Every structure is written in structure tokens, then in C-alpha cells.
Image (tube, coloured by chain):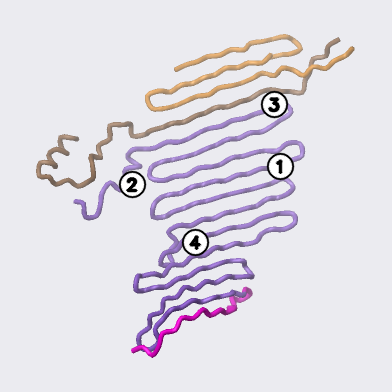
Chain colours: A brown, B purple, C orange
Amino acid sequence: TLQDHLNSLKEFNLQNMGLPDFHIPENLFLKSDGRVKYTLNKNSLKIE
Amino acid sequence: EIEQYSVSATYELQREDRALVDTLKFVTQAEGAKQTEATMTFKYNRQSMTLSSEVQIPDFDVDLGTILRVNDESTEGKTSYRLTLDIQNKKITEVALMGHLSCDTKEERKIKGVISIPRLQAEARSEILAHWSPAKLLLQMDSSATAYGSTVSKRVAWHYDEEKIEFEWNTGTNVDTKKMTSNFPVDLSDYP
Amino acid sequence: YQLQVPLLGVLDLSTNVYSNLYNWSASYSGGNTSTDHFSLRARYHMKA
């Protein structure tokens, strides 16, 4: 695609600021999935 | 074409059906065939506790209108309100702010904040709920916003139970390259 | 003397991170499965 960008640049006649060609992934995902769970059931141990 | 110049700050108690508006008008104008009315009027609805500010200067295309709406939904058993703010250039809301409060003193407690911008695709959401109960209090967090191909979401939920105690938190911040490119113009009117 | 001891519940934890070119998951569980029967199974697993 930079080849076509250069071909456009040959006449020094661009249409956009910069090069809209994107090397990076189309989707950029950053996520955090954390959880804390504890079973404090009321049951108990009887001791003598 | 003009007989005189007068600047006046005239107060008027205007009627809006049920409501009464303490209207104060500040106008600077020429008097005669030529009118130079540059008016800065400000109106308050003391029956709907609503404030409105108005300015007109056609020479510079000024027809700005700002409204601050407060609507009372509060009662002894429920403290509730609804806030609206209309940012209207040329009387067109290009920025709007809304809030909804619905707090049931018994169990429910709702808070909701919204930001919306139509022309810039900028939207922010801040919503909170707290369902009280003597046995336990249930908490919910909602805060999200979207603008120029960027999605922001924050979801944190906690709950207590005698059997177990449960807590979670999910963080979401995703961006799509093509979607952001389309949403954010990479082209200018006269640049090509 | 008679004493009642609340159980040491089962602890569940996991944080899973997902980013472009690198998805990572963590999962550990702790806490006695049965306080009054003395059963422990605490286990972890880290994966990148």
C-alpha cells in the first residue's frame, strides 16, 4: 500500500494527512478479568 | 435612522402557565429605524427552580441559549431528582448533560450520570446502584464511555452472603483501528 | 469445654489478562475443602 502512497506522492498530490495504512492489529484489546470468591459457609467444627 | 441610545436592565415577573419566571432583561440597542439590539436576557422559573440564560447578537450570529433544568422528585420516602443541562449554540444542543437520582431510603439507591455529544460521537456513562438491605448491602458499579473508536468499560460487582463472599472486577478498554479511523476524520475540507 | 470453630472456606482466585499477541490466565484455589474432615486440595496453574 505504501507503493500506491508513493505513486500518489509522485505528483506531490496527497489526499490525507499521513499514511492511513495500519500495521497494528485492527482490534487492540486490553482487558483485566479478576475475581475473588470464598466459601464462608456457616458450618463449623465442634471441638472438645 | 436613530433617535437615541438606551441601555436598560428591566426585570419582569413572567407567567409560564403554572410557573412564574423572574425574568431580567439586559438589552443594548439603537432606537429608531436602525436597531442595534444586543440582548443578554436571563430567566429563572422559581416554580420549577429552572434557570435559563439567553444572549442575542446577530452581528456575530450570536443566538446562544443555555438552560439549567432542576426537577424536584424528592419526597420523604424517596429523595429523587432529574438534572438536565442543554448547551445550545443557535438553540441547538451540541452538548447535553442529564442526571437521574432515585434513592429509596428503604432499599434502593440509584445514581445515573450521562454525557452525550452528538457531533463528536463522545458519550460518557456513569451509573451507580446501591440496593440496601439490613441483612446485606448490594453494590453495583457502572462507568463507561465511547469516543472516536475507543470503548471504555469498568464493571465491578461485590456481594456478601452468609454461605460465601463474592467479588469480581472486569476492566475493559478496547480500540478498533478501522472504526477509530472512520470515526475520527483523517481528511480535511481544503487539504486535498 | 466445647468450642465452635468456623470452617476455613475454600478460596477461589483467578486473574486472566488478554492483550494482543499475548493472552495470559492465572488460576489458584485454596482453603480447606472440609474443615471438620481435614481435606486440603489447594492447587495453582499459571499459563502464558
Which secondary structure, mark 3?
loop
Instruction: Relative to B28, say whether B106 is above or below.
Output: above
Residue B32 in the image: state x and y as whole percent: 38, 89
Disc 2 to disc 4, C-alpha distance: 25 Å
Quarter placement of the C terminus of chain C = top left
Q: Mark 2 = which residue?
A: B184
The reply to the same-chain question for discs 2 and 1 is yes
Q: Few, some or many C-alpha atoms within 10 Å of disc 1 (few <14, some 14-19, many ≥20)?
A: some
Q: Name the residue under label 1.
A: B132
Name the side, left or right, on which B105 lies relative to C30.
right
In this rendering, the answer to whether B86 lies above or below B165 is below
Residue at 42%, 36% in the rendered image: B174
Majority SS type along the magenta span = strand
Q: Do labels 4 and 1 share a chain?
A: yes
Q: What stretch is highlighted in magenta?
A: B1-19
Q: Is residue B88 above or below residue B140?
A: below
- Give the label on residue B164, or none: 3
**Whether label 2 touches label 1, CB < 8 Å:** no
Residue type at numbered disc 1: Trp
User: In the image, are marks 2 and 4 on the same chain?
Assistant: yes
For the residues labelled 4 and 1, the Cα–Cα distance comes to 33 Å
Of the residues shown, which amino acid type is indicated by label 4?
Answer: Asp
